[PDB]
Length: 88
Image 1 (cartoon, rainbow, N blue to C red):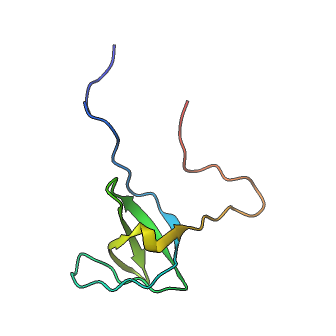
Image 2 (spheres, rainbow, N blue to C red):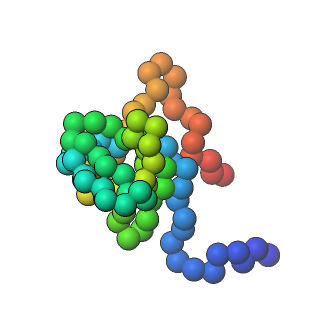
């Protein structure tokens, strides 16, 4: 008894909102791509298994190479984090 919706390997991960750190300034050319800056922080929203990531920078949004950024991560000071990973 199950619901066969995605009969394929892997999964689509989006709306993550994971804070990343631009280790290398990326130069975008297409409106779809985003220009990253070494020494800043972005917010990853989507992730393409291939390797390309999709986040925001200063209100902007586009595609950028994850190899340039790094998952900095930030924990909520005070009470242990909770909202996010939902499982049973």
